[PDB]
Image (cartoon, rainbow, N blue to C red; front, side, top):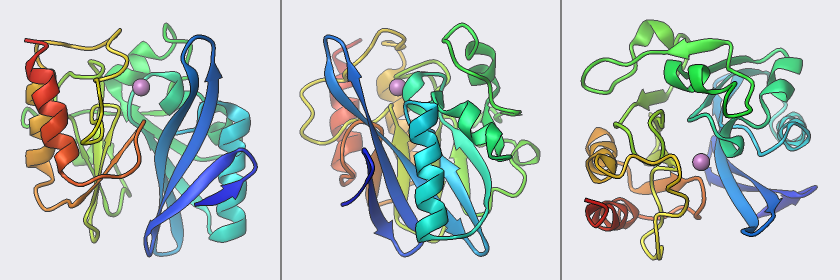
Length: 228
Ligand SMILES: [Bi+3]
């Protein structure tokens, strides 16, 4: 783990790093949130912001220092502060931003700034490719409503990594965490749909746990069975 200011960076594969930021949240302790940084040839792609603009600007500083290539775009995986809290920092840096159309719709009422571009999805869950131009190895998938109605997930082609965001919890998690905006009826199915979308992925990266095996998917889905 590389400590960089108050953030933590962890290399997961030759061209993939996890970014981690913390929010000292009254009543819940200091909460970690994870996203990804992916180098694709001569550019960098970001999955999710940090909790704040200042933290997100530090992600961009780390990228400048450690990779020193332009950030082509960012994709954010739902309209909550842990994933979209730093949108203004991205926009100030001239980075093109993408989110689920529904996330952009929800952003203002969630207290977030919307991304510049809206992803739409086919019936089977795969992103409509015209809406995700120049995504390179990022394979975007809407698994159905779960942690939130708008949650999306991302696989990284050329690696064994898939990012479940806030939908997936680790294999030893006691609970599904914050269910305030969750769809309790569809959660288990959506977690299983994520696993089926990225069947070869052996490292599952998540918003609020360290990377785990596919046991995170099975455990998450089993816990979600009890919400029905
Ligand atoms: Bi969240």
